Amino acid sequence: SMSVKKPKRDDSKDLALCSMILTEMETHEDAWPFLLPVNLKLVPGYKKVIKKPMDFSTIREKLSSGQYPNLETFALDVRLVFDNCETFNEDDSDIGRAGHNMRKYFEKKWTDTFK
């Protein structure tokens, strides 16, 4: 509350560390469904169904341009990528399996880096 603060957590390396995690996600072999925005002209249903499209390239550009105020807003967009993928894709599809795998991979790096 006013003039009453918990001790200051060092957040000065967060930007660098999120960039590193994002590099690791970009270079994973199962990243291909997520590298670029879904083509809303070429994929029926996507525009109407997925209210907030997100992809790794869009996260990389937001990250690079100071559009994440803190590491939680960064994790929210990463998780959005996988939540969208589960919304639109069966679990027993290549893309559906890719998304589960990538979510697992991300969540471990997140825990190991920050928790």
Image (spheres, rainbow, N blue to C red):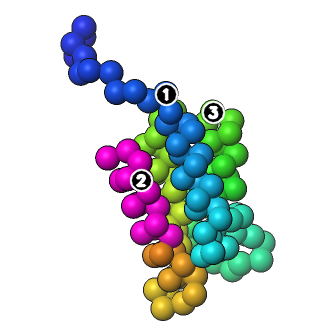
When the figure is inspected, residue 67 is found, relative to residue 51, above or below; the finding is: above
Three-letter amino acid code at the position of disc 3:
Gly
Q: Nearer the viewer, residue 102 or 86?
A: 102
48 in the magenta segment: no
The mark nearer the N terminus, 2 or 1, is 1
Q: Residue at x 71, y 64 (%)?
A: 36
Residue sitting farthest toward the front = 112
The image shows residue 86 at horizontal and vertical percentages of 47, 75
Q: Residue at x 50, y 70 (%)?
A: 102
Q: Earlier in the sequence, mark 1 or mark 3?
A: 1
In this rendering, would 107 be left or right of 25? left
Q: Secondary structure at mark 2?
A: helix
Mark 1, Cα crowd under 10 Å, few <14 / some 14-19 / many 20+, is few
Secondary element type, mark 1: loop
Amino acid type shown at disc 2: Trp
Q: Is residue 93 above or below residue 63?
A: below
- Vertical relation: 65 (above or below) 53: above
Q: Residue beneath label 3, please?
A: 66
Circle 3 SS class: loop
Q: Which residues are magenta?
A: 102-115
| Crowd tier of the residue under label 2, counting other residues whose Cα lies within 10 Å: few below 14, some 14–19, many 20 or above | some
* Image side of residue 5 versus residue 10, left or right: left
User: Can you give x and y, in whole percent of width and height, for residue 3 in the image?
Assistant: 24, 8
Kindly identify which residue carries mark 1.
Answer: 12
Residue 102 is at least partly visible in this image:
yes
